[PDB]
Amino acid sequence: GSSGSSGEGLDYLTAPNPPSIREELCTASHDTITVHWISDDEFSISSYELQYTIFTGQANFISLYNSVDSWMIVPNIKQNHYTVHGLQSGTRYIFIVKAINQAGSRNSEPTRLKTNSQPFKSGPSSG
Image 1 (tube, one colour):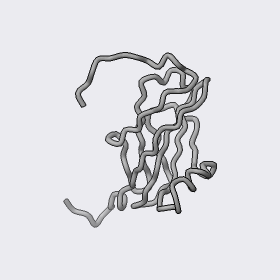
Image 2: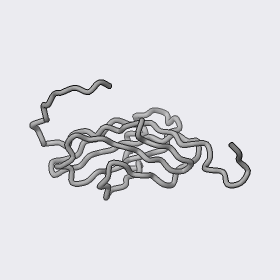
Image 3: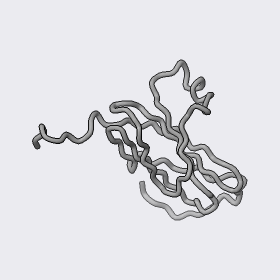
Image 4: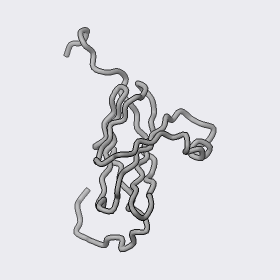
């Protein structure tokens, strides 16, 4: 990913810039996942919002995504990585970081993430 030298900056603030959910930085644990979101301008953002939901294969992505109200939300996020607790081993989980500022909010693209088989074994395990 050769880095470049260019600056534009969306003169518009009506809406908070969309965050970049890094999959290389994000981690997956037995029943815990740590999603990492990188942003260039988060000064306006008064607070971040995390939205995660279990993915199995609903009739249609639209149907589910439709009743977002159901989706889980965890406000009070003032970091660049929030560890979600209360998941299931070996299960799909879609995360969506929505930046919120004085203007409005910006929903980022859905980032699919899976957890690890099982947690660390205590006892029967050699390497």
